[PDB]
Length: 160
Ligand SMILES: CC1([C@@H](CC(=O)O)Nc2nc(-c3c[nH]c4ncc(F)cc34)ncc2F)CCC1
Image (tube, rainbow, N blue to C red; front, top):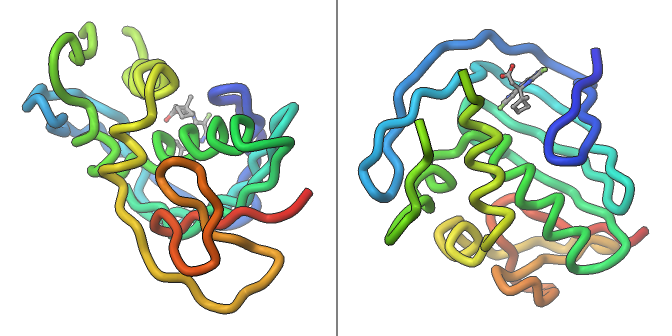
C-alpha cells in the first residue's frame, strides 16, 4: 500500500495508524482542521533525487535518515518529512504577513506548498540537537551546513 506526497513515493514498512480529524493552531493563531494519524509508523520515501527512511509517532518525527543528489534535493525531502510528521512546531512555523491558509481542499498539501516557498522559518523553529558517533551519517544545520556535532532534531544525512 504505497502513496504519493510532495514528489515522493511513501511505502509503509512497519506499524499502523488510525485517523482523527483535529483542529490545530498555526503561529498566526489560525485554526486548521487536519486528519491526524495516530500511531507509530516507519516509511521509505523514494523520490527522483532523494530517498529517506522516516520513523514517526503521532504528530512527532522520531528520526529521518536522508540521502540525496545535493543540499537542495535533501532539503526538499526534509521539508516533506517535517510537514508529513504533522509536528506542532511545523504548524507553529506558519506565521506573519500573508501566511494564512485559504480554507474539500487538503490542508497537508497547503502546508507543504507554504514551506516549499521558504523553509527558513520551518527549519529555525524546528530545533537543534547534539549527535552521537554514528559515522557515514552527518548532522545538518537549519541552513543546510553539515555538522558532526549538531543537527536538526532527528535529522541525519547519509551518503549516496
Ligand atoms: C496525501 C497525504 C495523506 C492524506 C491522508 O491522511 O489520507 N495520504 C496518506 N497518508 C498516509 C499516512 C500514514 N501515516 C501518516 N502520518 C501522517 C500523515 F500526514 C499521513 C500519513 N497513508 C496513506 C495515505 F494515502 C497527506 C500526506 C500524504
